[PDB]
Amino acid sequence: AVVSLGVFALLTKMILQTPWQLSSVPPTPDSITTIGQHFFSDFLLPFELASVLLLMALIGAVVLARRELVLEPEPILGEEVVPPLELPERPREP
Amino acid sequence: AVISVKPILLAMTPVFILLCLFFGTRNGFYDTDQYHGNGSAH
Amino acid sequence: MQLTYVLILAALLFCIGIYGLVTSRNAVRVLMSIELLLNAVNLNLIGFANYLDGQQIKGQVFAVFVITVAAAEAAVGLAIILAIYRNRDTVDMEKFNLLKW
Amino acid sequence: NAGTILPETILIVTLLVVLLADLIQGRQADRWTPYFAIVGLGGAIATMIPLWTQPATISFFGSFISDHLSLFFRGLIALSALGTILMSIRYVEQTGSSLGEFMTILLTATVGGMFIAGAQELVFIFVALETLSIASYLLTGYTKRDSRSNEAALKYLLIGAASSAIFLYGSSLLYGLSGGHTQLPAIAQALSSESLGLVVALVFVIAGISFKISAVPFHQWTPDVYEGAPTPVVAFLSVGSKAAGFALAIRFLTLAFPSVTDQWQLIFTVLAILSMILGNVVALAQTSMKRMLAYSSIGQAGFVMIGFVVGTEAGYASMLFYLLVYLFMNLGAFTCVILFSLRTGTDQISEYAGLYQKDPLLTLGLSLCLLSLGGIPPLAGFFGKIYLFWAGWQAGAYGLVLLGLLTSVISIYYYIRVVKMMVVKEPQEMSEAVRNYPEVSWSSFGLRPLQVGLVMTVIATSLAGILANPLFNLVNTAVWDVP
Amino acid sequence: EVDYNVVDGVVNLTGFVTMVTGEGLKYLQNGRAQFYALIVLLAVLGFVIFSVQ
Amino acid sequence: ATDFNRGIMKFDGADSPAMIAISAVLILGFIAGLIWWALHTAY
Amino acid sequence: STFPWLTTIILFPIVAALAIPFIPDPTGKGRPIRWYALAVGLIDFALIVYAFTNFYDLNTPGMQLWESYDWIPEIGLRWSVGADGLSMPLILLTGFITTLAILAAWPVTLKPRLFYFLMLAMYGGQIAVFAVQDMLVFFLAWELELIPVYLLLAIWGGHKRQYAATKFILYTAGSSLFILVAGLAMAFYGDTVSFDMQTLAAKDYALGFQLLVYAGFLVAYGVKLPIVPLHTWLPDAHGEATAPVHMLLAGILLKMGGYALIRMNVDMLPAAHAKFAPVLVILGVVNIIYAALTSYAQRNLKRKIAYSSISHIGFVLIGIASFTNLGMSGAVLQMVSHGLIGASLFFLVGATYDRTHTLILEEMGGVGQKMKKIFAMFTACSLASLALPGMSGFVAELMVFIGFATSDAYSLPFRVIVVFLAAVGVILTPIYLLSMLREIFYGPENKELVEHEALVDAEPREVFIIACLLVPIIGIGLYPKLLTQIYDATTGQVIARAREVLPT
């Protein structure tokens, strides 16, 4: 509660005293047309990387939440013993 | 009028070399009792 | 409502998200408290776009990508909690301190 | 104008081909699909040599630059994922996980970090930082039944998405202090006043820049991620996710903030004089090798900042080269931990004791990558640290090099302790592999990619300092595009 | 005995106050990932009081 | 120090920690007393 | 002349050390790898005497094998080598004692593929220190014998190897950093970034800067040459070690800390010397009296001579900081003569202990009844270290006493007390050497002779290595212009470098 109240009193001192250069022009000339001419001129490579980020977010979030009903008791191989779907460094206390 | 060390070193090199390669072949006790064995100061 | 009052709204909406990020004991309430931080950087961002650079909005484009990241970070983010709940049958952030030192 | 992101769009094609072969063929494809990612990453390196001679174009309407430094840091991040696929071809295939779904996340974090090193706008930095960071949470909890990777996946998310919220709050004010202008060269002409808004915009972005590199007030995730995550992921988060954070620290702080410049050379000093301390003294009382190599990389990130805060043409060139030889040490140290963890379980120190007569390629391998990290001659990490302290001593900084030397002696003690418990322990003092080593083969699935992944790093560890005059000219020529 | 205990006592004290410095900051990490989020957030508050003066 | 009191001409009996400090201040005082001599007596 | 001679001698063992895992026939203990490592030692000692008797061209001050190869132009460093008079006695000594250290490393069957790799790598890592005229190669070569000598003491050592091995790598790498710090302080002074040892000497420094570099160098060179407050790494690293390893530590590795005092604290920083030189001779006097009483009070046998090697070193400090051509010519002769004497002592401690298995010096007595050639050899080498005339121990200390109290630098009440105090070491060295000889060999009271000490002999190879080392002890001690002519003209310029500054 001190760091959160500390950041808040820090940011309000920053907000008020900083001179912003606010312009008196009328905004939004149909802001679905000038937001779509940004997706395919300037913000194109963040728009194509948003596709790569979302495909990875579906590959990863499926394999971390799906049920292991394919083979839960699968002793695949061995040099020394490893449990299924676990990293082989077994826990051990010195 | 000083004895130079170069003719006394160059004439002492090939006797030092030929004597190590002979005296390596001749040794005793470091192969038969030798209870130090492997670990050389244990 | 001017530009200044949106920022102090965004700076206050950030710090309730911070207080939930550190104090909350449910593993899911930390994820909702993360989403408050990713709205305060949106409320700052559109408010910087309306009063500054109003003709070509570079902020409302940048406001779109924050929603899609945080929607993809909460889709990943709950997959992790749902992998823990199948192993450790509780969600308690004072129970995940087994990698101590 | 899209000929400059050609190294990344050979990896995006390779991202889909190693994914589509997983759905079509289904775990019979793991016999051939790791070797297609190698020729995709190697094909991504091989097309930057036509781009190295190009005169540093600024493509994609000002959202991506292809300078000489952006060609360099795109080389290490693809090479670290080249070294990781060489390790992980048997490791995660031994866990029982599908091997095609692991590489599709890893070759997305690779394309994430390749797009940080050349980004030039405030939005393309954030999305590229996200897709490297989102894919890094999924890899650290990828084994998904471990009760250690589960608690290391969550410690990385509640700090990573936290610091990706602090980083966005500094990106948003930087859009607000300037009158719009989300591009980085358009920012620096608009703000020059050095007011309080610029400083809060500066500390809020280096709370997210200096989280990937694990500076020591923000280092807290690294020792608790690294012992929970699968070990090839750890081999990428120490070289790939650090060269990506060190590439952002030069593309941001030299472009966005050249007006305020006495301050981020002072904050990164306090991150440098304190990560050398707590990286090195806390690694002493660590038992696990994956947790010893965690506090090394906090401290090894403190040596790189010595070249950063000095601000000379020999300064930044000294931190580019030190990352170039740090790739040849952690990928040869983590190769041997993996190679020891696959043969026997519990890869920790005081279980290495009794080697050198059972698998002496590992023991010769792991030694030259641990000794070089401590900086003994003639290996690569001696010649890497000399150019740091030649860069620190050139322009001020008499106390930064000296803290980097008294803590380069404490670093000797915990690297030697593994080399002690490999080669000096007698055959009456071995705990595991007391005739329990698996009688080494190098003939099973994917072991021969590991054997070539270790020999081509130990050769590249021992000879990188003697043959450093090519690499010193490749790195000093990548610095003339840094203001 | 002034050799083995005084000038050997200083050298065996540099190696003792660095091993017990390591076991003092080994306790800096304790799990509880919210405490790690404090130190990230406290250092943000620290460096903005550090660098404005 | 028990291996320093080996069963030959040693073990004077003054291996006590009260003697170790009072032997140190004369020995380390003589070297310091000779070094501080040197910078003022030689030139 | 065009052929790189010193570049060969540095790199030929390390190139041929790597061919040791490819040597075939591991049929039992390591016999063929013992003979390959010995022969590759001897054909590099022949390369030193070929390069010396044809190309050295003595009574000329300067280097006569000057090969400055370009290595990395960005840092400013080159691969420069060269043999002057302050180094060419010591290149010859290193190629002589190491070739016997391979031959004294004959009974080792613990890890013989690893032993002879590091010893050949240490044979290159010692000649490389004396030869290079650079500063980032000199810091390379200083710590190039850091990892092979950690492993030589840890695997083949006594008990408390590991406490002695890690106390040593932490204390030398924890002191080698002042070579880099002071080597970079002179490199960036002025306007040039030159790293050669000539331009860093021929550069003019300020006086207040020179006292920071000298005190930085003093701790980095007071560790290896054990100036007696900074000396605690030695009697553990020398106490718990084997005799073939120990000849490379006490014979040669201590000499690098004294070689580098003459090169880099007397040439390069003369007005820094003339201010803090009387602290050296007082640290040279106490080096003799402390280390001779510490040697007497010790009952571990290998630890008695280990503390004795600090005492013979104590004349190098009086020899360096006396500003006389006979003082400095008596210090270089002290470094050569102690290497030949200290190798002949430290071999026979291992030659005694390998038969009686004790080192405790209380369970002994009557060792000279069983082994006689060990007794006859250990008397002639301990008599060599008494500074007894007719051997090179006395002529090396005769020039220091004469050279110090003939200088027109110090005052007379100082020179009388230092010569009176350093000559107490004349009384003190027969106290512990002859009592070591008496409580081992002389006497009727033998051991139990049943459980321990079942054997006694003297191998006809081991009689060579002492009679190989006792020839140049006597041959220098009977005509010391067999050595003084090698470094007469180069030492005569170092003193000419410090005489023009001296009233300061």
Image (cartoon, coloured by chain):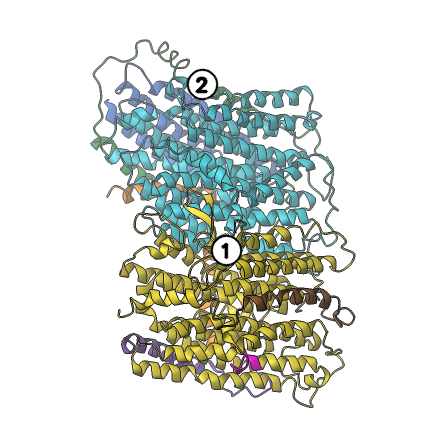
Chain colours: A green, B brown, C blue, D cyan, E orange, F purple, G yellow
**Magenta-drawn stretch contains G329:** no
Instruction: Answer with left or right where residue D183 lies relative to residue G310.
Output: left
The three-letter code of the residue at mark 1 reads Ala
Residue G455, compared with residue D47, is above or below; it is below
Q: Please name the residue shown 57% across and 23% down the image.
A: D15
Taking the view exactly as shown, the residue that stands out farthest to the bottom is G444
What is the x, y in percent for residue C29? 46, 34
What is the x, y in percent for residue G301? 60, 78
Within 10 angstroms of label 1, few (less than 14), some, or many (20 or more) residues?
Answer: many
What is the x, y in percent for residue D145? 62, 37
Residue G265, compared with residue C61, is above or below; it is below
SS state under label 2: helix
Q: Which residue is mark 2?
A: A47
Instruction: Answer with left or right where residue G430 lies relative to residue G16.
Output: left
Q: Which residue is mark 1?
A: G141
The chain carrying label 1 is G
The three-letter code of the residue at mark 2 reads Phe
Q: Closest to the observer: D142 or C1?
A: D142
Magenta range = G383-392
Residue G424: give its label: none
Quarter of the image with the C terminus of chain D is top left
Q: Does residue E31 appear in this view?
A: no
Please tell me in which quadrant of the rendered image residue D88 appears. top right
